[PDB]
Image (cartoon, coloured by chain):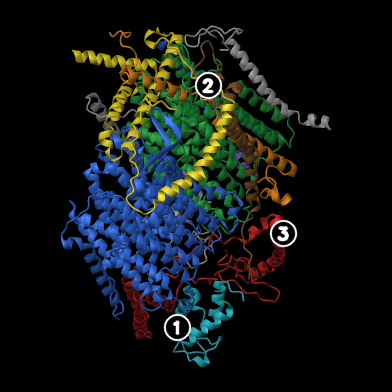
Chain colours: A yellow, B purple, D green, E brown, F red, H cyan, I orange, J blue
Amino acid sequence: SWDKDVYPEPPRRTPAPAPQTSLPNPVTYLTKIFDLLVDRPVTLAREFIEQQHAKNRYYYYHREFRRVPDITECEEKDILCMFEAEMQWRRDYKVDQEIVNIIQERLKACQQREGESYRQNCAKELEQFTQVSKAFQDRYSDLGAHYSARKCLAKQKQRMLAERKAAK
Amino acid sequence: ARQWQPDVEWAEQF
Amino acid sequence: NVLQIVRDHWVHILVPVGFVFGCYLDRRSDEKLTAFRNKSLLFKRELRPNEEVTWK
Amino acid sequence: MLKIIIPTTMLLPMTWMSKHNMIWINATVHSLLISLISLSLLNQLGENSLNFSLTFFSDSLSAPLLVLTTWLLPLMLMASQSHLSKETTTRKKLYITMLILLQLFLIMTFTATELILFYILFEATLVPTLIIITRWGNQTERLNAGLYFLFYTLAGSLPLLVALVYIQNTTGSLNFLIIHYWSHPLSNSWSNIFMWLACIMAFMVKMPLYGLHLWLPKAHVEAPIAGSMVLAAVLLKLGGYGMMRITTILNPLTNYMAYPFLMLSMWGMIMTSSICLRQTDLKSLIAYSSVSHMALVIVAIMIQTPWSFMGATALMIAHGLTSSMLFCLANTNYERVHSRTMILARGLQTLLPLMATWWLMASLTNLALPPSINLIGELFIITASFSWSNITIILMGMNMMITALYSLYMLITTQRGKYTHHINNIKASFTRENALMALHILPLLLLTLNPKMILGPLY
Amino acid sequence: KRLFIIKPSGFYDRRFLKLMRFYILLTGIPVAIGITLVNVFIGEAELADIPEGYVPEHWEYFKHPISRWIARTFY
Amino acid sequence: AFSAPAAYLTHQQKVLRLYKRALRHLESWCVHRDKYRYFACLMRARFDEHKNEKDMVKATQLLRQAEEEFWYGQHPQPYIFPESPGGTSYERYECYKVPEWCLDDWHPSEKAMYPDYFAKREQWKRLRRESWEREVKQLQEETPPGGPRTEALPPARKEGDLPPLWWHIVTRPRERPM
Amino acid sequence: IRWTYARSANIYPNFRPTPKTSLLGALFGIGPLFFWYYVFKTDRDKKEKLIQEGKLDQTFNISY
Amino acid sequence: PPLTLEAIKDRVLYVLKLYDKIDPEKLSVNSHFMKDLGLDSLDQVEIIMAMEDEFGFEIPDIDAEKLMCPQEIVDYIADKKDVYE
Amino acid sequence: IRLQEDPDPEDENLYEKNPDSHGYDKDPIVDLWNMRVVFFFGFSIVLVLGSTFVAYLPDYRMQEWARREAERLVKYREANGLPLMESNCFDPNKIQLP
Amino acid sequence: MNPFASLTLTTLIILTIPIMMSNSNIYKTNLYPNYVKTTVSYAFTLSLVPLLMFMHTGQEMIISNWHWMTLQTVELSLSFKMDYFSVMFIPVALFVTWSIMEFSMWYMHSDPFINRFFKYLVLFLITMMILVTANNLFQLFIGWEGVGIMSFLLIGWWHGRTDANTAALQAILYNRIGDIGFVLSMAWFLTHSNAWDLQQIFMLNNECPNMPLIGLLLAAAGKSAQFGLHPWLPSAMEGPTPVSALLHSSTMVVAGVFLLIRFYPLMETNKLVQTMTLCLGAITTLFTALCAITQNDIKKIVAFSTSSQLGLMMVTIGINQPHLAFLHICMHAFFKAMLFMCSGSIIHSLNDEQDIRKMGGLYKAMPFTTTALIIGSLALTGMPYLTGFYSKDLIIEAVNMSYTNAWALLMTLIATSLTAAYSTRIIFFAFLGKPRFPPLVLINENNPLLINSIKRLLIGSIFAGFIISNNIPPMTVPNTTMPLYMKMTALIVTIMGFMLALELNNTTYYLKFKYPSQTYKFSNMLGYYPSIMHRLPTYHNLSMSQKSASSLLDLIWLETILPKTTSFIQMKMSIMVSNQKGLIKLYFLSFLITIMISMTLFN
Amino acid sequence: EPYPDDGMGYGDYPKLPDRSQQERDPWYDWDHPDLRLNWGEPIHWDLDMYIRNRVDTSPTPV
């Protein structure tokens, strides 16, 4: 049920069977035996369980957090606003970690899927992960074990001052 | 074996 | 022989009663800290009909 | 947190008013139920701590330690039953009361939200531990060990009290939440340097640091089985918990000031693991291994990186379980042969087969066979140190090799070879001892399946 | 020409193993059966967008049924 | 079963031990039986050549030189009997050996499985318990005033008396216990 | 018992600060610590210098 | 391989009979090599080596020198191999 | 030097009086009930029920929530051409540089 | 494709069922070993299916079934890499384990804890399967350490033997010294590539640096008993012969070569690491073959041959020919396992006699074992169109036809000659000649288990190389054209070694005695590496521990510095303060002094 | 012979010959067979180092 856009997979191109020999193919008969002995019972069991699940269907919801004022707009020593903003920053930290995870999963799946042509046919995913890794490292790397919204803000300010100096 | 308890020599030091 | 059983095995009621009492006192302390029950900027909602507190 | 605290307090009246026959049974049952209650604390919101009240809060760091302490109490009672059988009812009740007071103090220390209250409870643990060691120890050196333990810890702690009062005066609050949220950076001045030293040194003493670890071997060797179990599993971990908590205040100076303690811990781990190779007493060997693992934990804390902190938490829990189990396994042999000399009892695998398997599992965990939580913590610490310096791998790998060597040397000497001929008092292992070893081992192996529970807040 | 084999008493270790297995299974087998029944019949919840004007209860944000029950009962 | 050692090894015993060591190492070097027999007869002739030397100093010097030759000519990997010290099977069955005192700790149900054996064991226990006092008395009587000057133990002087300190030798675990 | 006592308890009572004991203690106790300080400090300082000069590769080093 | 006492005696007498210096006819279980037969010490060493090669177990030198008789060799082998019949 | 009682022999094996000692006490009934209490309330209850409680503990760590939010953000940003992860954690405008 | 994953996972999971049933009554019953053997045989039969699917369509897969834990941006999950290496090695290892267990049933029948022996063997197989079928460095480490621990347990099967315990500790020590490199590689990959999965590691590390490859090389040297860490494998023969044949002969030792093969894409980039691997392989081959030449224990000879073959595989890796290295692993499994089983049969027949000098004239006494050993030795020495010919002949030809360190190539050729030499040694001393074993003759090879177990491996040795080589897809460009002498170099060297070994062995018959040469002492004493290396470092480390860390610092100097000195100062001050004089005249003067000093100092 | 009085803590303990337990005669019936040691015998200061498993000082062929 996973979204294809979030988890892209290249279209599957499977060569058609083109036997050139009289000898029976063992894999075909073994696979038919597997289908009959295993796949059919498994499919029937899953059919029964899915019927049971459909009999009592209940839903769970994905929580939505409204955006709250950031640390930049929080006054000094304003522990309420600082607490709200820091919790928001931590949630965003987790979300960015998950984003990096998704891109890395794309990377590994591409490495496996392409095969011996991984170096060339996986370039786009590698570029995506390179961009994401650079962004993530700049935003969150080196903050330390006691990472806080204030420290990330200070790092961003340091980076911006360095950029202004580069502007000269 | 039993837990060591002060002897006379140990007591005499005090 | 109940009188005998309870008279010499009543000590087994102390700690569970302690758990019950601890739950009660913790709920009281939650009562004390209700200032921003629904005054946050994240979970602040309009009380749904037939509701007086969001228990927060 | 009162859901746990109040029942623990009620444990004392139950123990005192229980019948002479039923003291151990009631204590064990209700302590186990309390431990079951503590498992609720493991459910931790990722972003924020569980702030139960102004006084008490729990996070992904305190929760595992609280669970460990609550679990440890029943195992301690089970282990201590045997050697206290001759003792009078009042003394047995006093021993149980000391254990219960220790659990209460440790729980309040772990859940306390104010550094001054944490200090009061963390120092308060000395009294029950000191009483246990110096009243129910079996050797003449129990008194000297108690003096060393008490004075090392107090000499470390008192400057911490002065520093905490000074912080209260300057920042205005010692509540951990406020300290974390405000947390102004420190400056590199001699006064701030000495404040950093005052904050760190007490926990550095509690977590046996090379040069400040002398108390640990004496105390663990000379203490009764329960006291050794608490000291290894929990009392050492108080230093790690405090150091992880206290490090927020000392942000910048930690880089400059870490090098002495970092070098001391890194070299001391090798030194103590080597010491274990040539030790002639089983308890002393276990204690020195504890010292080495806590040195790894100290390195993790000083580096101040998220992976290092996760490894530190995992290692703390895993080591507490493994060291307690090792002490209990040694105590069984001590009770049977009434000596702690490793050479005296040999070939015990033939005589006591299942205890041999318990020893094997404990030693494998000690040498960090994956996917043990011990290995998870050690590996995370090792990777964090590798980021800190690639050269760190040499010492850490050497320590891993030495740890494997000494663990399997203990296993080979005690449980392998020909049985000591003259010793005739070896008797079939009791269900109690095997149950204690299983209660130690099974939670440790199970915790591997879900390791996020012991990976700490930074997870 | 059978010869007696001198070995340590195995009754106690075997007894402990039997008791440990019995006490583990006493609640495991019921627990395993309960888990299988719950998953087979009650099933896991389906993710659905919050209907407009509805404020879900805290337990309604977790997929698994037993997790929902734990969240409702104890948290 | 090992006999008590003596304070020193006599010159004859040292020569005999050298002879045995040389023959065994030669057999190690001479894998095939025929070559071994030929060179072994050679070695026997070598010993016979100075078998009858009258001067003890000369014989001692000869023994010393022969030992030096042996050390130079020792096989780097001499053959070791499989169960001998250094052998592949030395102490292999040690773990299977279990002391007799362990049976006393058996649960009564376990002892029930082998009733006749435990009846015989009780008989042997009675024999030891009765014999201990007389054995101690005999050891005291035979022992010289200074003390035992050798590890050798006296045999039973009179009928109805077991050899002193006999229990562990008699009841030693079987070589292949299984 | 004598072996265990001599190897644990009797050591300090029969120890006297001597030239050999003092020098060996100094060397084998504090010597290694300063060697490891030199090594780690030099390595760390070099790493920090490279980072400052932007001449170190951390392209995918996003997990410290 | 029960290795009964009679088998041990038979094999020891086998080895000794195949020994040229010993004349087979006068060889007996109680024929001391030193006294009844004419074997010297080195012959004692050789015979002990032959026995240990025949049974595949090494007789320690201290015990080896004291045998001085075939029956002694048989009983010592029985003791080492735990032969009770 | 003192009148003291002889050192007690090694504590009598609980097996001798009761072969099925189970340890835990001299009295067999208390031994059995102590073993039963330990086994039940630790193995059956704490380990099995506690392990199940930990295994199905509701995900308040927000791992699934984080994954869902990340999926939404990735889809939206890729659709709109915006970079997958912005380099600035906080919007530059709000910051007032010195 | 759908059946592939299910069958591949079921093959591994089926093995665990006997371990789970160890708790049940079957463990007590005699049926447990047969049940374990039957489980292994069924697992092999199932494993054949995925292998056939791969042969048909190259249906490689990666299965991440369970998500263990997500650590910030790093996800650790249980992932199985069902690629060519795993899909082929699983059947070979399962077949070898099947034969070895059938043989063990006969060999270990007398052993009281036979059920424990079989259970430990199944555990080792499970750990090795984890090692082979791993897509994460952490899961591979689980397999690595599990194999090490199982080797420790099985090698010291007889706990009574002090030698066995020493061998187990030695194996653990050397393998841990290797594992230092494994930990280094894991740390480097996590820190730089931010992943422990092989796929991301390959993707990011286009040009792999040196440090992680050197750490992997150290781990491979530790597991495969390369020079400097080689002693543990020969000492491992202290364990029961089935344990040696299964783990320390054909399956466990190959782990390091398998570790390097798994990282072959990274290995190609770095030239220095390839050269180091080649040199280490050459050193191992030459040294181990030379040591084996003069060894008088059959198990020792076979173990040194295994070490030399591992060195040859490492050389193949150094030549940048990994798939040939994997093929050599596969074929060595068969023939070396068969050889060790034959040695076990000889040992059992001759009442636990392992010295070749005491074994002779067994060619007719044991016809089937003699046939199995002859076939195995021919395959090991590269006899054409046997299992060895398909792997070793290609390895030699590729080594010649490539840019190579000259001494490495010379050493490899000499090593092949020495392999022929020691095969001749075993055959000549044991099977040929006149019987030198003790009089009572108990030779009886007529056991169905022994005969069938050796039969399966004999058929595999004879025919497997052809089948595997033909079926596997071509993975290297062949060295089509080469000088005739280059092509025949392997046969020429092997035959020369055969001739020289046979000539020297015949000279032993001659009634001439010469005192040992220095070279013979060097070879027989294993190069003196054991004598000096196992004594000088151990003595210094333990003595340093006791003399310095335990006493000079812990018990003397630290105590003197912090505690003792402070206590002494306090005691002296207490003696000063409590002068115990109590004279009014004395301390009232102090009052006067205090008053004057106060007036001056404090105004 | 006592250890030299250099303040290293050996004190009265005898300075026995530095021989590994392997060197001791295997055939003798030692009180403790595995350790090749006798009851009441002075125990070498470094016995744990010199046990049969651990360092061996036995004479070598070369």
Residue depth check, mark 3 versus mark 1: number of the one nearer the observer: 3
Quick check: D406 above or below A121?
Answer: below
The quarter of the image holding the N terminus of chain D is top right
Q: CA distance from mark 3 to mark 2?
A: 63 Å
Disc 1 on helix, strand or loop? Answer: helix
Q: Does residue H40 appear to the left or right of H73 in the view shown?
A: left
The residue pinned by badge 3 equals: F112
Question: Residue J598 falls in which quadrant of the image?
Answer: top left
Residue sitting at 59 percent across and 9 percent down? C53
Q: How many marks?
A: 3
Residue sitting at 26 percent across and 27 percent down? G48
Residue depth check, mark 3 versus mark 2: number of the one nearer the observer: 2
Q: CA distance from mark 1 to mark 2?
A: 98 Å
The residue pinned by badge 2 equals: A60
Query: What type is the residue that disc 3 sits on?
Result: Ala
Subunit bearing disc 2: A
Q: Which residue, as the protein is rendered here, is positioned at the far bottom?
A: H25
Q: Residue I90: x percent and y percent?
A: 34, 14
Disc 3 on helix, strand or loop? Answer: helix
**Label ID, residue H41:** 1
Query: What type is the residue that disc 2 sits on?
Result: Tyr
